[PDB]
Image (cartoon, rainbow, N blue to C red; front, side):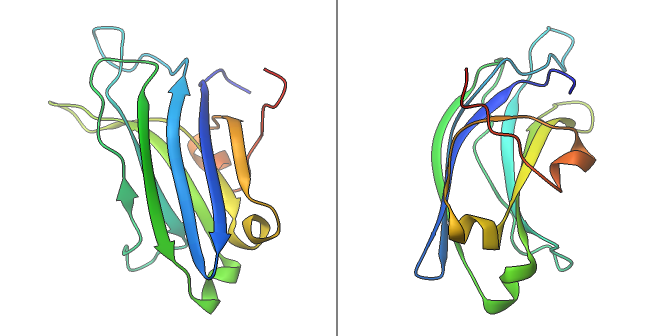
Length: 138
């Protein structure tokens, strides 16, 4: 429930391809000494034991309201029926390990049946691997 902010994204599956658009995020949590963060988004299909599926947006420095406007494509295989699209926002740090900011996920089979679109509530790191929470209300 902790206020980690929100992210706007689209995710849909067409002809065995998963297309994801990471638009923007709002009200992220300060994670740097200067009171801001340097956010980027990591996308993966999990589980990913070999660590082969990772894609990420650019890092946007010094903001809590990043606008990435980036799109990504994943080629799907039959085994992806048991997988989830994981979306994690991280804070890039120059002098320390990067900080986790917030996350969420979508089942691949669930996206096939209905694309994701709109604002989603950011969850904690464990939480985010399991579900998502749309915020259609505002």
